[PDB]
Image (cartoon, rainbow, N blue to C red; front, side, top):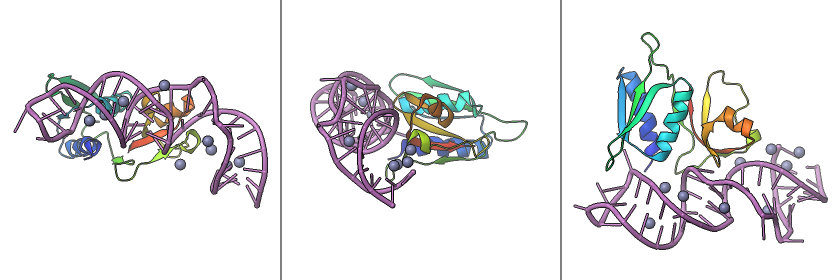
Length: 127
RNA sequence: GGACGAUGGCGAAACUGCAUGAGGCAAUUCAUGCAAGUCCCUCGUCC
Ligand SMILES: [Zn+2]
Ligand SMILES: [Zn+2]
Ligand SMILES: [Zn+2]
Ligand SMILES: [Zn+2]
Ligand SMILES: [Zn+2]
Ligand SMILES: [Zn+2]
Ligand SMILES: [Zn+2]
Ligand SMILES: [Zn+2]
Ligand SMILES: [Zn+2]
Protein backbone atom coordinates (compact mmCIF):
# COMPACT_ATOMS: atom_id res chain seq x y z
CA UNK A 1 0.00 0.00 0.00
CA UNK A 2 2.75 2.47 0.89
CA UNK A 3 6.11 1.27 -0.40
CA UNK A 4 7.86 4.51 0.71
CA UNK A 5 7.01 4.04 4.35
CA UNK A 6 8.70 0.59 4.16
CA UNK A 7 11.82 2.35 2.91
CA UNK A 8 11.70 4.83 5.71
CA UNK A 9 10.75 2.26 8.31
CA UNK A 10 13.55 0.06 7.14
CA UNK A 11 16.09 2.84 7.41
CA UNK A 12 14.70 3.94 10.80
CA UNK A 13 14.92 0.32 12.03
CA UNK A 14 18.31 -0.39 10.52
CA UNK A 15 19.78 2.59 12.29
CA UNK A 16 18.20 1.67 15.66
CA UNK A 17 19.72 -1.81 15.46
CA UNK A 18 23.08 -0.62 14.04
CA UNK A 19 22.68 -2.79 10.90
CA UNK A 20 25.34 -1.88 8.38
CA UNK A 21 22.95 -2.31 5.47
CA UNK A 22 19.28 -2.68 4.67
CA UNK A 23 17.83 -4.19 1.53
CA UNK A 24 14.32 -4.00 -0.02
CA UNK A 25 12.47 -4.35 -3.30
CA UNK A 26 13.52 -1.51 -5.53
CA UNK A 27 11.52 1.06 -7.47
CA UNK A 28 12.59 4.04 -9.59
CA UNK A 29 11.12 6.34 -6.94
CA UNK A 30 13.01 4.56 -4.14
CA UNK A 31 16.20 4.89 -6.11
CA UNK A 32 15.48 8.56 -6.62
CA UNK A 33 15.05 9.05 -2.88
CA UNK A 34 18.13 6.97 -2.14
CA UNK A 35 20.04 9.26 -4.46
CA UNK A 36 19.07 12.43 -2.55
CA UNK A 37 19.70 10.74 0.80
CA UNK A 38 23.20 10.05 -0.44
CA UNK A 39 24.07 13.49 -1.78
CA UNK A 40 23.02 14.83 1.59
CA UNK A 41 25.21 12.71 3.89
CA UNK A 42 22.41 10.39 5.17
CA UNK A 43 23.54 7.03 3.73
CA UNK A 44 27.02 5.85 2.53
CA UNK A 45 25.83 4.17 -0.73
CA UNK A 46 22.92 2.45 -2.49
CA UNK A 47 23.00 -0.18 -5.23
CA UNK A 48 20.56 -2.36 -7.21
CA UNK A 49 21.05 -6.18 -7.65
CA UNK A 50 19.41 -8.74 -9.98
CA UNK A 51 16.93 -8.15 -12.81
CA UNK A 52 13.69 -10.13 -12.09
CA UNK A 53 13.50 -8.94 -8.49
CA UNK A 54 15.61 -5.79 -8.26
CA UNK A 55 16.72 -5.56 -4.61
CA UNK A 56 17.83 -2.08 -3.43
CA UNK A 57 20.71 -2.17 -0.95
CA UNK A 58 21.33 0.86 1.26
CA UNK A 59 24.52 1.17 3.23
CA UNK A 60 23.69 3.10 6.41
CA UNK A 61 25.96 5.70 8.01
CA UNK A 62 27.36 6.01 11.49
CA UNK A 63 29.29 8.90 13.05
CA UNK A 64 31.62 7.12 15.46
CA UNK A 65 28.86 5.09 17.14
CA UNK A 66 25.73 7.03 16.23
CA UNK A 67 23.11 6.88 13.54
CA UNK A 68 23.45 9.83 11.19
CA UNK A 69 19.70 9.86 10.48
CA UNK A 70 18.11 11.20 13.70
CA UNK A 71 14.53 11.06 12.38
CA UNK A 72 12.99 10.19 9.09
CA UNK A 73 9.27 10.87 8.64
CA UNK A 74 6.67 10.33 5.91
CA UNK A 75 4.81 13.53 5.09
CA UNK A 76 2.74 12.81 1.92
CA UNK A 77 1.02 9.34 1.84
CA UNK A 78 -1.64 7.66 -0.25
CA UNK A 79 -4.43 8.59 2.13
CA UNK A 80 -3.34 12.18 2.58
CA UNK A 81 -1.37 13.68 -0.32
CA UNK A 82 0.73 16.79 0.60
CA UNK A 83 1.88 19.29 -1.99
CA UNK A 84 3.63 22.70 -1.73
CA UNK A 85 4.21 25.54 -4.13
CA UNK A 86 7.75 26.90 -4.41
CA UNK A 87 7.06 29.68 -1.93
CA UNK A 88 5.39 27.35 0.55
CA UNK A 89 8.35 24.98 0.89
CA UNK A 90 10.45 24.95 4.10
CA UNK A 91 12.00 28.40 4.45
CA UNK A 92 15.34 27.54 6.21
CA UNK A 93 14.22 27.07 9.89
CA UNK A 94 15.08 23.42 10.59
CA UNK A 95 18.85 23.74 10.53
CA UNK A 96 19.89 20.45 8.90
CA UNK A 97 16.57 19.03 7.97
CA UNK A 98 16.02 18.39 4.32
CA UNK A 99 12.61 17.78 2.86
CA UNK A 100 12.66 15.41 -0.05
CA UNK A 101 10.48 16.81 -2.81
CA UNK A 102 9.14 15.27 -6.05
CA UNK A 103 8.94 17.90 -8.67
CA UNK A 104 8.22 17.84 -12.33
CA UNK A 105 12.00 17.94 -12.86
CA UNK A 106 12.73 15.02 -10.56
CA UNK A 107 13.18 14.12 -6.94
CA UNK A 108 15.35 16.71 -5.14
CA UNK A 109 15.78 18.47 -1.78
CA UNK A 110 13.59 21.36 -0.72
CA UNK A 111 16.67 23.65 -1.26
CA UNK A 112 17.18 22.44 -4.79
CA UNK A 113 13.54 22.89 -5.62
CA UNK A 114 13.57 26.47 -4.32
CA UNK A 115 16.50 27.15 -6.56
CA UNK A 116 14.75 25.73 -9.63
CA UNK A 117 11.61 27.69 -8.89
CA UNK A 118 9.41 24.61 -8.33
CA UNK A 119 7.11 23.13 -5.70
CA UNK A 120 5.91 19.50 -5.66
CA UNK A 121 4.86 16.60 -3.47
CA UNK A 122 6.63 16.38 -0.11
CA UNK A 123 7.78 12.76 0.20
CA UNK A 124 9.50 13.00 3.63
CA UNK A 125 11.61 14.86 6.16
CA UNK A 126 15.02 13.63 7.20
CA UNK A 127 17.18 15.06 9.91
C1' G B 1 -1.33 36.31 2.33
C1' G B 2 -6.18 34.62 1.59
C1' A B 3 -11.41 33.92 -1.79
C1' C B 4 -12.41 33.42 -6.71
C1' G B 5 -12.92 34.17 -12.23
C1' A B 6 -9.91 34.50 -18.41
C1' U B 7 -10.58 31.60 -24.55
C1' G B 8 -6.21 31.10 -19.37
C1' G B 9 -1.24 29.04 -21.66
C1' C B 10 0.22 25.72 -27.36
C1' G B 11 4.07 25.56 -20.09
C1' A B 12 6.57 21.10 -16.91
C1' A B 13 5.88 15.87 -16.37
C1' A B 14 8.68 13.40 -10.75
C1' C B 15 4.54 11.79 -8.09
C1' U B 16 -1.19 10.82 -8.16
C1' G B 17 -5.16 9.62 -11.23
C1' C B 18 -7.05 7.74 -16.08
C1' A B 19 -6.04 4.60 -20.51
C1' U B 20 -3.30 0.78 -23.24
C1' G B 21 0.43 -2.87 -22.98
C1' A B 22 4.14 -6.13 -20.47
C1' G B 23 5.25 -9.00 -16.06
C1' G B 24 3.35 -17.49 -11.75
C1' C B 25 -1.14 -12.18 -15.16
C1' A B 26 -1.95 -12.21 -6.60
C1' A B 27 3.08 -7.41 -7.72
C1' U B 28 6.32 -3.19 -2.84
C1' U B 29 7.03 -3.79 -10.90
C1' C B 30 7.97 -1.55 -15.73
C1' A B 31 6.89 0.91 -20.78
C1' U B 32 3.98 4.50 -23.71
C1' G B 33 0.26 8.40 -23.60
C1' C B 34 -3.15 12.17 -21.45
C1' A B 35 -2.88 16.45 -18.55
C1' A B 36 -7.90 16.10 -14.19
C1' G B 37 -4.96 16.28 -9.45
C1' U B 38 0.01 18.59 -8.58
C1' C B 39 3.82 22.33 -9.97
C1' C B 40 5.36 26.97 -13.06
C1' C B 41 3.72 31.41 -15.43
C1' U B 42 0.27 35.36 -17.42
C1' C B 43 -4.29 38.77 -17.07
C1' G B 44 -8.45 40.32 -14.22
C1' U B 45 -11.23 41.02 -9.95
C1' C B 46 -12.68 40.64 -4.56
C1' C B 47 -11.11 41.17 1.06
ZN1 LIG C 1 -1.66 24.01 -1.38
ZN1 LIG D 1 2.48 32.06 -3.12
ZN1 LIG E 1 -0.84 38.96 -2.46
ZN1 LIG F 1 -3.66 35.28 -3.50
ZN1 LIG G 1 -7.33 28.30 -14.61
ZN1 LIG H 1 3.63 17.06 -22.78
ZN1 LIG I 1 -3.14 -1.58 -15.75
ZN1 LIG J 1 4.05 3.78 -11.68
ZN1 LIG K 1 4.22 7.74 -16.25
